[PDB]
Length: 423
Image (cartoon, rainbow, N blue to C red; front, top):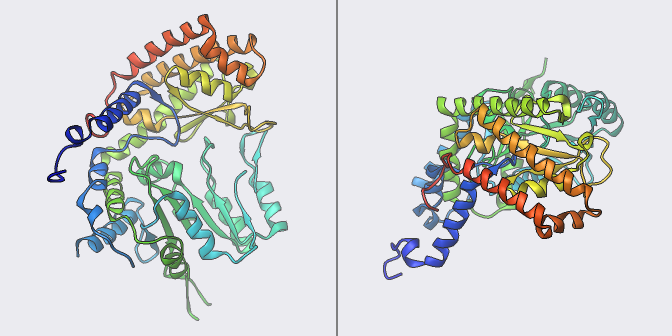
């Protein structure tokens, strides 16, 4: 401006109004995307700080990165002699790419979820096949992580397969990292060589990445102490290889979120996510829905809509038009990625708005009503695009959607919202 200290509301009314509109949209909806959350003000304040002016690569800043490093190992209860962390990755993908480039040579073999497979009878990771398949394939790295699994991963059993075929075990804990930090679920750090995470899902911060790696003594020869050798390879893979200088503002925002994750209130939040997820699952079962794996031990539920007669693409779109955001998801035995059988629902985002179990029972009631409209509409229409345009162009459907929507939004608006008041 004249000063560069003018408020956004005063200097750019058009942008301010876009932000107020987006804010109103978040406040009036029911966010059930299992990977979503609402960032705290405090993290956002760091992100928009004068650290944006400070450029670095390789006084206060280096204190920030070291601080962030220290807070990362602390949040996850890690010994700095046994674990290091690279806090510089921009997002979650750089974290993961940095890993594969660091550790593997061209056309090295890799296994991960898709590949190993879920047992369709139990909807659990088929650990038996993983171990047989990996004896065949001799992978150099195996990735433990998924975005759509409602159970706890047996990291110990994957460490067996890895210890056997001399593979690295990478745990991608992006979706469950807050739960791991609060110690409400078991920790992959006990069994894994490498752990990657984003910071914007259950950690409830900004959109950045972390790479944790084993350092120090791996073993003793019975030359003497045999060391881990991930550090210099990971570090080099991050900078200068895959990235430029770190966003110091972004690293500060990460540090603020990791500090929050250490507090008793964060543990209570995390416990409540598990309770809310179980409540959601029970309410769905009580109304005769099928759940992949028959329920949950974490932050999400995976609904198999196929016995009900609707698919996840259809359900997802109806729910969207009544201000309920969820994601379609493949189920075991599914044919089509376009019309998957399932709907993934998560507790983290609404738990951050102080929803309790009874509030999740309410959400389920609304979801049930939406699915019912989807079943009506599916009965009167043919192709997926006919289904979609009917929702908009049929008078009776359009009016039923509007009534459920007004009711959803009037319920949602009453709950608080993390972040800044107005934008």
